[PDB]
Amino acid sequence: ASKLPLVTPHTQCRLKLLKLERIKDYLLMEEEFIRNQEQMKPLEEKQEEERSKVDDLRGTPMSVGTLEEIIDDNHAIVSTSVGSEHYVSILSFVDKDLLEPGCSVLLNHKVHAVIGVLMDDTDPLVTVMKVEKAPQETYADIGGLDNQIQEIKESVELPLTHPEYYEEMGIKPPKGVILYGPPGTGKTLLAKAVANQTSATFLRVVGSELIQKYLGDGPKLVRELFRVAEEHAPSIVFIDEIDAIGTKRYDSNSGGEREIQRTMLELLNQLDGFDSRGDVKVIMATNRIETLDPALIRPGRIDRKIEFPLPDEKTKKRIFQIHTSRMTLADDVTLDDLIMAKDDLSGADIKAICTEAGLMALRERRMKVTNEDFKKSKENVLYK
Amino acid sequence: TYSRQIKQVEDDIQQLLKKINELTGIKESDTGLAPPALWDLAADKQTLQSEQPLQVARCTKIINADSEDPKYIINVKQFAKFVVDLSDQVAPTDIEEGMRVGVDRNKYQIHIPLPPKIDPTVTMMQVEEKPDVTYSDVGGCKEQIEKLREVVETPLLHPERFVNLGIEPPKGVLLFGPPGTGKTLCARAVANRTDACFIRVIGSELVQKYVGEGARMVRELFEMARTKKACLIFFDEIDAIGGARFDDGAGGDNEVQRTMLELINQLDGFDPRGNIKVLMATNRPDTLDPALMRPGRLDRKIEFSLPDLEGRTHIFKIHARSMSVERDIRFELLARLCPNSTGAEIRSVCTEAGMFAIRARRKIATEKDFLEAVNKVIKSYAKFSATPRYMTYN
Amino acid sequence: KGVLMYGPPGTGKTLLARACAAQTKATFLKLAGPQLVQMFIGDGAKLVRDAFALAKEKAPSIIFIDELDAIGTKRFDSEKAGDREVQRTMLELLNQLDGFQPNTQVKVIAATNRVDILDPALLRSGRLDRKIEFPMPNEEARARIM
Amino acid sequence: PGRIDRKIEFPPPNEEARLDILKIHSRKMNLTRGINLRKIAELMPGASGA
Amino acid sequence: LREELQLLQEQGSYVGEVVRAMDKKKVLVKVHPEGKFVVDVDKNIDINDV
Ligand SMILES: Nc1ncnc2c1ncn2[C@@H]1O[C@H](COP(=O)(O)OP(=O)(O)OP(=O)(O)O)[C@@H](O)[C@H]1O
Ligand SMILES: Nc1ncnc2c1ncn2[C@@H]1O[C@H](COP(=O)(O)OP(=O)(O)OP(=O)(O)O)[C@@H](O)[C@H]1O
Ligand SMILES: Nc1ncnc2c1ncn2[C@@H]1O[C@H](COP(=O)(O)OP(=O)(O)O)[C@@H](O)[C@H]1O
Ligand SMILES: [Mg+2]
Ligand SMILES: [Mg+2]
Ligand SMILES: [Mg+2]
């Protein structure tokens, strides 16, 4: 295990033959040394004789307690599971490194001495926020933007996949990225393409669930979010619909607008605090960019500000080519009449028509979609 | 030539490492055990020494002593209160009242005094580790640094120039300006160079869920701070901890004002804090309370304004001293294009213009690579700008 | 029985209270305002009657309360919400000072810097008698202060 | 429009639909022969199914 | 029948709740309001049956 990290010649040289044959002698001499322990001092079997001695030391009932402090001369104040806490001692088979205040431990039943530590069963909120698998298809599913698809790779993908271009420049990557525009243009759609592509851990939270019903439970939820994001990996924190923290007032929140405010002060800390930040990239998205606090959008917290426009009428035709790719489309239809139907139909409307017109065909058990399917589709989707 | 011959002689000896380390004992990936050849000290001896002679000594809390006799009144977590006595191994000296002690399970007598409870959410806000911002990175505001550095560290590094002159130096200082100006940046340089404990407090951490729970956290801060010989408290974003008392009708934000009042009492009056120096940093000072803006608490009122011209030209030299540039560019021309800009924006210009070199192919930025960055950062992100409604501090 | 000092925050209110702690050789007892606020119910109320019973025992004693607007905030009628547990500690401090079973053994010195916040139930005449104010120093006192 | 897949309206019932709601809920009642539930359903001018 | 006079003096059995098992033939079981116990299994009970 991690015996030698040198692999650098990478050929059929004698140097690769020399190094590993040196290591061959460092292993056998270490083998033959430790072999002569049991030859002259048998004294045990050591596969079980030390083990069963430990297993007979530790009692068969094993109570579970809680750490709250350590005094490093192998005795610490531990809390029992009722609430009455003791001043028991710690053993030597305890590996006194995995002990934090709040870690669940194993105790003796007789004198309650700290026998072993317990691996924690965590968590019912990490698995909530952590995206399990890659969501959907690739960047080729998008179509039409092609100017900011370069931009997001520039700040997320390319700092991760090519860590040589910023070094030859002598620069650090831009920190924050926000995404804004009208509703239904592809803000949430682009973030799935990033989570398809990346090898980082990807955390998502919606801005509406940042507000809590108790006092101070809001800023506690933010502090432990960035704790989770930092403790894993190079990671990507995606916060969607963050204007919703300030627009909608809910009667669950006992603190009024001045509990929204204290949460945003904590969020204002966690992006550009004084603490050592680490490798965490922040992506944000909204559709009401003018409402939120300008102190949160200052450079240093969010560097890149990407606008999404409405789909142009030659980018619209590309979107119909995507959502009607794998459907058995009858040759009656003409897509170019469908394009200029609404003058500002978003990319969401195109999928809203193409999914609905397929639903009309299954009412009549058909397999191909005709023209009058689309004729009654935009009446159903748009006009109400 | 010897393609497989260097491979299989490599591969078996990498296996022969594993094939005999399984015959020593590091294996059986545990549920909380030790490495096997590390606990051998307590294998026979301290097994029957740290367990069989040694006892459990359940820990308690003492109410009071009484005269003429030991006769201590003790208290435990949920059970009763007892009348106890000492052991032979401790003097009756350091068994002073209101102190946690360990107590056997049969006779109920006191074994050893204990260090008190530290309330661990205050334990996590001691910094333990220093950041890497030097005063050489806070260029452009030298006069503000000098007027700050003479309060925080010069009575600590030389506590004799003041005493022989007979003056008591100031204690409190707040740092205020528009955002992105250098307040949190200049606070990191102080924790770089200093040597006392540097306990940081973000003002959004004192909002608690119960009533008066936020005010007890202020004390446990100032209890462990008085134990130290010198400590340096840092308050950040204190517009959340208290603006002003305005109580009207339905008592709203009454809870946060009591936390703001307990902080006021720990700063002045009645056997003061001693050698504790505080340091606030806010974004809008006009909301703050007049009894907190009073000197004797917040003596120094250092301003962080925008850089003038030579503040700006110095900041370009800081954030572009470490990047591959064309030799023949002038920074003084660039700082005339950013009239009311912050130091955080100037760093974003320098990082953006290095990206344009990465956009096409090249390895060193040009002067026109800078100018394509200025009109994007200064003039195309000017819809947001964050400054002009904070210059008036509203 | 009961004195009250008020005014702008830098006029010197604690400075008289620290002066009297050095002059008389009585049992001086001091309080913070938000110290009488507890998470559990009835503990801040219990903490008031424990303090006055302690100053009852040391019969020459005076009690000091700093920042009285922490607990003495004016009561208000509202549904659906509002704090209540703070008023219980106030309403015993009204009673345990003055009312049923009164005493002349302890003297109260109270100090705040804002007055209009306070409940008129604690500014009656019998609970806090002599309400003195501290004006800002006019001209001549500033020559004496510095 | 891309958010909700299909919206379904529930109107108040008419004369043909007030009859069979009566027909299902008169199942568990011990009736008398000769009722003419049609005349009963027309007296309610579409209240609801409740 | 006359065995139970010298059978019922044996103390009763607790009832608990399995969370999950682990290495080397043990399970993690919690009691009513009492703390979680790492206990071993008997020989007549399969771990995958637990
Ligand atoms: N430019 C586009 N190209 C292809 N599909 C698109 C485009 N824009 C939107 N869509 C389709 O619309 C659907 C929803 O888009 P999305 O929700 O990402 O828009 P949005 O702006 O994030 O919406 P909101 O503003 O409500 O968050 C996506 O599933 C996508 O298939
Ligand atoms: N005078 C300066 N010299 C060099 N860098 C600066 C200067 N001012 C700001 N910066 C840059 O600004 C960033 C830190 O800003 P800081 O967090 O101090 O803003 P602030 O004044 O605390 O306002 P906020 O509280 O909104 O953050 C750092 O990235 C730093 O490089
Ligand atoms: N002669 C004086 N008159 C007024 N104030 C003084 C005088 N001498 C000193 N002081 C200052 O007044 C302060 C007293 O604080 P004080 O006004 O009582 O605070 P608060 O009223 O907010 O409790 C002391 O810090 C002291 O330095
Ligand atoms: Mg979306
Ligand atoms: Mg800051
Ligand atoms: Mg005072």
Image: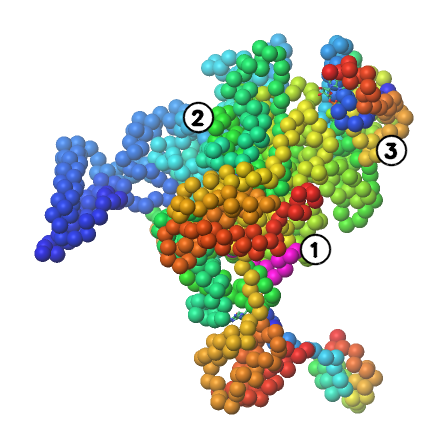
Q: Is residue B297 visible?
A: yes
- The disc at residue B55 is 2
On whether disc 2 and disc 3 are found on a single subunit, the reply is no
Q: Is residue B83 visible?
A: no
Q: Which residue is mark 1?
A: A249
The residue at the point 46 percent across, 15 percent down is B89
Distance Cα–Cα, label 2 vs label 3: 60 Å
Which subunit holds the residue at mark 3?
C
Q: Position of residue A315 (x, y in %)?
A: 51, 74
Relative vertical location of residue B337 with respect to residue B182 in this rendering, above or below: below
The residue at the point 37 percent across, 57 percent down is B361
- Name which quarter of the figure residue A133 lies in: bottom left
* Image depth: mark 1 or mark 2 in front: 1
Q: B223 or E4: which is nearer to us?
A: B223
Q: What secondary structure is found at the residue carrying circle 2?
A: loop
Q: Which residue is mark 3?
A: C120
Q: What secondary structure is found at the residue carrying circle 3?
A: helix
Q: Residues within 10 Å of mark 3 (few under 14, many from 20)?
A: some
Q: Position of residue B385 (x, y in %)?
A: 61, 50
Quadrant of the image containing the C terminus of chain D: bottom right
Distance Cα–Cα, label 1 vs label 3: 35 Å
Marks 2 and 3 in Cβ contact (< 8 Å): no
Residue B147 is inside the magenta segment: no
The residue at the point 54 percent across, 59 percent down is A306
Mark 2 CB near ligand 6 (8 Å cut): no
Which subunit holds the residue at mark 1?
A
- Amino acid at pointer 1: Arg
Relative vertical location of residue C27 with respect to residue A242 in this rendering, above or below: above
Provide the residue span drawn in magenta.
A280-291
Q: What secondary structure is found at the residue carrying circle 1?
A: loop
- Amino acid at pointer 3: Pro
Q: Residue furthest right?
A: C125
